[PDB]
Image (cartoon, rainbow, N blue to C red):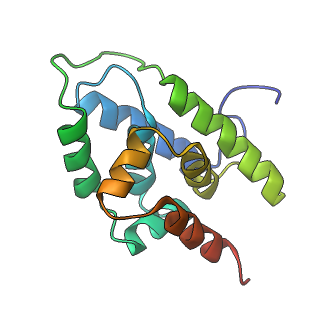
């Protein structure tokens, strides 16, 4: 609500966004799309989102390969800040809604992944399906990791 786009993000969730930007830059991409957020979630390596994805066999190299196939490497590397796609912004908005509903005042890696699945229609969703990870199964893995405590 108040403040910066990223005020509520945990340290790990902030690192997801930093990594997403660098993953877009490495592909010579002109936006940070949902698939770069997916790459950042895995790349971050420690959070609930990375754990959920890797335990389903979704790998950083597998996602990078699928993105290069579907989207293709761009011609020129962007310099500076790379803007979000409209879909990636919607994912980030949904991540806040997921965190609020779950009773938290922070947005963690789990909430970004749940927001990504809820949007369910962009490049990340296309890649997860191509790799054999159904969106509902990814959601189930996250919820399982958040439950049972």
Image coords of residue 133 (percent x, y):
39, 64
Instruction: Decide which of 82, 87 is in the foreground and name it.
Output: 87
Q: Quadrant of the N terminus?
A: top right
One can see residue 104 in this view: no
Picture residue at 33% right of the left edge, 19% below the top: 30
Above-or-below relation of 109 to 141 = above
Query: How many circles with numbers are drawn on the protein?
Result: 0
Picture residue at 69% right of the left edge, 48% below the top: 107
Image coords of residue 79 (percent x, y):
30, 15
Q: Is residue 32 left or right of residue 105?
A: left
Image coords of residue 19 (percent x, y):
40, 41
Instruction: Decide which of 29, 117 is in the foreground and name it.
Output: 117
Q: Is residue 2 left or right of residue 115?
A: right
Q: Work out which residue is located at the far bottom of the displayed protein and give it.
A: 148
Q: In which quarter of the image is the C terminus?
A: bottom right
Above-or-below relation of 77 to 51 = above
Above-or-below relation of 86 to 19 = above
Above-or-below relation of 128 to 132 = above
One can see residue 60 in this view: yes
Picture residue at 19% right of the left edge, 31% below the top: 72
Instruction: Decide which of 146, 21 is in the foreground and name it.
Output: 146
**Would you identify the image quadrant in which residue 109 lies?**
bottom right
Image coords of residue 100 (percent x, y):
81, 49
């Amino acid at each position: 609500p108040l403040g910066s786009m990223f005020e509520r993000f945990t340290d790990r969730a902030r690192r997801v966004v930093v990594l997403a930007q660098e993953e877009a830059r490495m592909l010579n991409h002109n936006y940070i799309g949902t698939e770069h957020i997916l790459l950042g979630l895995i790349h971050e390596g420690e959070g609930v989102a990375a754990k959920s994805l890797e335990s389903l066999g979704i790998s950083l190299e597998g996602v990078r390969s699928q993105v290069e196939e579907i989207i293709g490497q761009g011609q020129q590397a962007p310099s500076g800040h790379i803007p979000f796609t409209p879909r990636a912004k919607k994912v980030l908005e949904l991540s806040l809604r997921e965190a609020l509903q779950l009773g938290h005042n922070y947005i963690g890696t789990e909430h970004i992944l749940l927001g990504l699945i809820r949007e369910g229609e962009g490049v990340a969703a296309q890649v997860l399906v191509k790799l054999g990870a159904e969106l509902t199964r990814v959601r189930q893995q996250v919820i399982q990791l958040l439950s049972g405590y």
